[PDB]
Image (tube, rainbow, N blue to C red):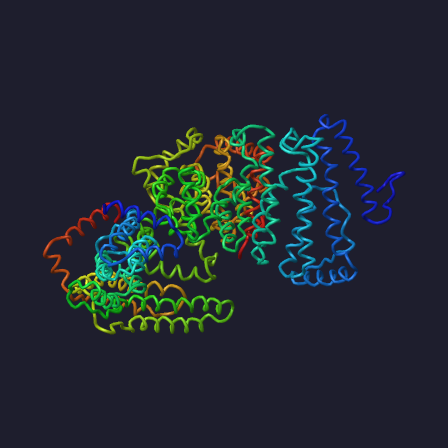
Amino acid sequence: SNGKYIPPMLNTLGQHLSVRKEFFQNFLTFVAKNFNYKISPELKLDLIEKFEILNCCIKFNSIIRQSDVLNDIWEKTLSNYNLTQNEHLTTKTVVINSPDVFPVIFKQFLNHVVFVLFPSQNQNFKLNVTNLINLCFYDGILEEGEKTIRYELLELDPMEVDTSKLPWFINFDYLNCINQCFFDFTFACEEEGSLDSYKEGLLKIVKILYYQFNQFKIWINTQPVKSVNANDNFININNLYDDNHLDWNHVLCKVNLKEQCIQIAEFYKDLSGLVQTLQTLDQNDSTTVSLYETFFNEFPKEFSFTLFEYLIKHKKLNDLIFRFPQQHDVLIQFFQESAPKYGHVAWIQQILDGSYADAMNTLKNITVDDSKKGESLSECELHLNVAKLSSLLVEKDNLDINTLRKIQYNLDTIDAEKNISNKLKKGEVQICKRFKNGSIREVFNILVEELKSTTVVNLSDLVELYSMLDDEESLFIPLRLLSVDGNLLNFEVKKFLNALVWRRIVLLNASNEGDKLLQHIVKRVFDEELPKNNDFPLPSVDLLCDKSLLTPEYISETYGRFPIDQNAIREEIYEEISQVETLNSDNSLEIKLHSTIGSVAKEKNYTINYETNTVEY
Amino acid sequence: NESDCLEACSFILSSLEDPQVRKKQIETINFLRLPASNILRRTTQRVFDETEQEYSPSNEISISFDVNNIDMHLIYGVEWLIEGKLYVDAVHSIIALSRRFLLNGRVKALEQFMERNNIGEICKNYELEKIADNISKDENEDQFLEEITQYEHLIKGIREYEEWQKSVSLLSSESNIPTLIEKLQGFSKDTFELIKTFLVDLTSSNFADSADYEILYEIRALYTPFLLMELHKKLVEAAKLLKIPKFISEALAFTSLVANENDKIYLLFQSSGKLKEYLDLVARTATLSN
């Protein structure tokens, strides 16, 4: 509000603001009228942004400003609720200022409301949350942009040629923040216990997601084949899919929020939410049940398969069997026709027709229970029982982390030797396709005689060696060694070894057009809660390649005492360093990485360390 | 044409859904309880045919405890008859179900079957029906109640212990762990006695069929001993949760004690071999790893 003839804000805050808004609007009307398709969808889009912001900030403010009594009440109620979360922030007239951003203004607001929403019972407050969400996030972008601006006159959507994916303002951070929000907001509507009111909130998120994915494919046009040679956002919020969708629809069924099921399913493309609503019935009303029977013949795979997902997964097996006689034949077809989202529900039906699944316990009872050991070892049972009891000092799953390591270091060596040994005996040899070559393959064959024997060798040697070998157990041997026993070494030495397990993975990854491999292994680490146990660095993209943790210790541990050709190793290391950088700086490839890392980190209430690496002492 | 009716009817009844619609249509398609039997039987048959492929393969006494969804469909075949007021056919038909359950070793299928329907009523009503039909029969009067049913006391035992454990953990959330052990010790002991108490015999009767005492012995000879063996490993299992000094000799002594068997299994070994087979299997284990 600077200028020769632009006042530093006349009058009512809303009145000057409207003046300003006229100016921004006018500029747009002029880009639409004359210059619409001759101007890139970058700069113009920034004029749209002005409206989005303004709309959201003022609405919130104005509700409270109705009467003088309500405003005075508001200040007390809001201040009091802040105290329960140990924070403070009262609003009026310190809101409205309308900083130029697109979703970010919404993001800030939303967090703040949800924070002091769990203590809140205020209704002015409840009301205020809905208005902020809708105006900025749904309405700003789609209903004050795409519908009423692009699709009439001005045009150039974010699926027409932008920076290299989307406009300048939209970056990786925004996409990742959306992914988080989906699940945190689903939790929140159970919490207030008025799930129903927050359908609308939910609707906006699912809508925004669907639209976005379309933007990605249409920007390059066609079908996935350039997103399958380089993963991006088009699968980054179909991670939380399966489990959560089906759960949330089921929670909604019986509490007769039948509409709420339908939206979630519709945008992510599954007939299951619609079909499950209809089916919610015991079997009541002959007419309706008959109608469902008609639909079996008319759609023998599509309707049929979707319907089974409800009944098998939620075990409403009575409906499945008698009620539907003609669906037994189709139930076999379902097992013979699976992969998209029908394998996951089909196994359960199969093991439950057999009525046993106790096979897993028998095999477990030999190896976990100290009752059947060796073939001429005695005293095993006694040691093993005493050992389990000591690591029981800490409550529940988490064991005393210091006691664990002393046993673990030598065990993981014996188990590593033994795994390849069973393999060698069969006359089978384990190597990767681009690690087939050179000095390591030769060294490996000398070592084959050695691995039969059992002797304690260093974790640094083992880490390096194992990661280049095939097979799941083999690849686990580097992750195992470090999580537990890596914290017997220095912090800097722990991280550098870690980068090295990661680096080999990148090599393999980079060599194939498989881009999902790195994502899965990063995800896996938080599910086994390795950073909570014994300290293990958390997955970062500034953890893959380390080179600022120059220790001579690291040199003498890895390459100074493990026998592999120096020339070769050095060459591999140069190559490793290049490949990590490419994924870390190529736009698509950062989107897949950033997105995936940040959501899992938030849900688990993790913090990336570069010291201690303690997420649970 | 008996076949043609049976099918058209069975399909009509199934294709009319809602439990009340089923109830009345089945109830009022009966008279004389001798050829009304036949109409319902094909409805019985489709109910079984669907779940037939999903039904458990045990047709002999073995491991198979607890009702699943597959069982319940089979129980529903009998429910069709009860709704029809077909007590003539039903008295026979109850005994036949109970025998299949006994023979395939499903004490739990029978037990649950026994809650929803009871034999004893069925035999008394039978007699009254043949006063209006006047078909000859021998005195079939029954007063049967459960007494097969010592398994409910097993499950009762576990649950109190389990309740301590939730509550015990709650108490454990920073308090004093030794006091919690005293209580846990109290619970295991009292539960262990409790399972051994309670006897259901009551009025003495059978299923309205004799020579079924043999069948009941075999079913017991399986599940019963299996559970006993499991429990005999259970002491060891529990003795590995909280750190405690000594108290190892008792276990040692029990182990030693489990050497004075008393039925003659070695005599059985002498009779036909496998004791031998057990050496062959040991030798193959030793040549792989010693």
Query: Farthest residue in the right direction?
Result: A4
Q: Position of residue A6 (x, y in %)?
A: 87, 40
**Does residue A379 sit above or below B195 in this rendering?**
above
**Does the image show residue B253?**
no
Residue lying at the far left of the rendered structure: B271
Relative depth, front residue between A84 and A332: A332
Residue A193 higher or lower than A505, as above or below: below
Residue drawn at point x = 61 percent, y = 30 percent: A219
Residue A139 visible somewhere in the drawing: yes
From the viewer's side, name the closer residue of A563 and A381: A381
Residue A78 higher or lower than A184, as above or below: below
From the viewer's perspective, is A137 left or right of B43? right
- Residue A439 drawn above or below residue A522: above
Q: Nearer the viewer, residue A151 or A342?
A: A151
Q: Give percent across and percent down for residue A490.
A: 54, 49
* Residue A514, horizontal then vertical, whole percent: 48, 33
Q: Is residue A102 left or right of residue B173?
A: right
**Quarter of the rendering occupied by the N terminus of chain A:** top right
The answer to which quarter of the image holds residue A551 is top right
Callout count: 0
User: Which residue sits at x=66%, y=30%?
Assistant: A162
**Horizontal and vertical percent for residue B32?**
24, 59
Along the horizontal axis of the image, is A73 left or right of A591?
right
